[PDB]
Image 1 (cartoon, rainbow, N blue to C red):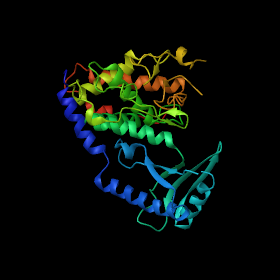
Image 2: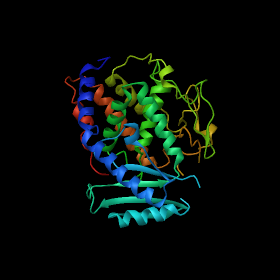
Image 3: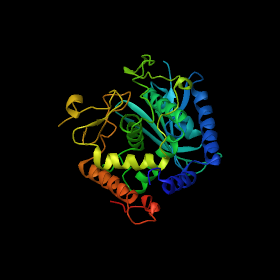
Image 4: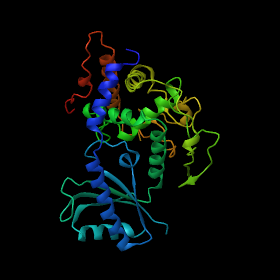
Length: 327
């Protein structure tokens, strides 16, 4: 009811079903090891770094790898790396848009992997490596973050509100919505803001400050004793009824988490849902969200709150993950 015992038990049971298996994680590490050898051929000085969900442990079963090629010196290596992969029996796309190259491996011919093999490779994407570090740090700080993030991702995918190409929000946007709630909304806070810590030292990477208090062993445990179910209950309630998407920005650069679109200059490339990236401050993670997309997102937050506040016991908690029709 307050510690939402039956909802918490339900949440952990689902988390154990949707989290990545030991088998799948070992296969993706095997795939990274193979791809690292192809890059070594072209440049022994180049580095293939994994980032995103799998590196921060926030991945759902059957995930896609988000890789990055770190060069000191994209310059020539991108087209050269793609050539080697094609020659090694890999299928995929090479995309060259806005002077930035991307490799999208769609399949594998003759290796220890199959056709279901999907993998994205970027070049000198240093900022995404830093967002992964920040997210990893927070998971290492409290054991409730990983199940909370996975369950919100599973819910967003099932309710069809996780499509940045169809007017809704990316998985990364939901992670930042979860973190924002846990740092600046819930009382007592679940986490401190590591970017605004007095122990934070400046670190400039690609003209953005990527510094945060990363000495985690010295950060005390949370002062908030809420169960996983209670945490999720409050999250859905906040974004369903309390958060003002018209005038406010989800931010990690204000001590009280209070920031208006007017102050940011994100009024009148969309700013319908405003989520300020913690490092790339000029980037709105919610820029893909349309007005119709925001109404579906709020619509699903309200349905989630309604379910968790039903008067009719038992509560059909499974309906939270029931697949919604394609819009």
